[PDB]
Length: 63
Length: 51
Image 1 (spheres, chains in turn purple, orange):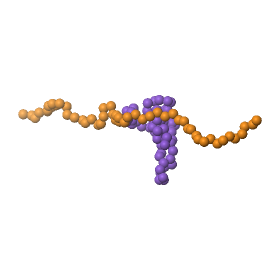
Image 2 (cartoon, one colour):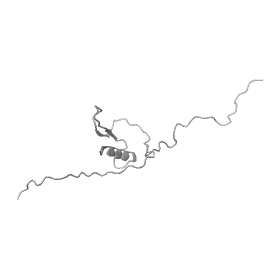
Image 3 (tube, chains in turn green, purple):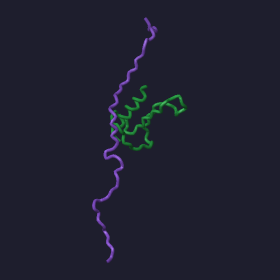
């Protein structure tokens, strides 16, 4: 019950360039249900070879 | 005079620091939507027949 808020807080840091979260960290939160969905858990990638793309973040308008 | 095991703790507290959510405004774009291509005013014909 803290994973959603943590993911949203981390996404707000990267967007507003707060803390030291790299502007390009991927905060992923693969939810867990009872179904055979992808393995659950909060990943956070910041490695130097991933592909990224810009999108206008609504609720903040901060790209 | 040594250290002995004491009573088991009755509870646990886990502290974390968390900020809150703002209002949903959802300001999608500076100049938004795909603005349509359109007619230059008046224009005028730039060609005539012979005669």
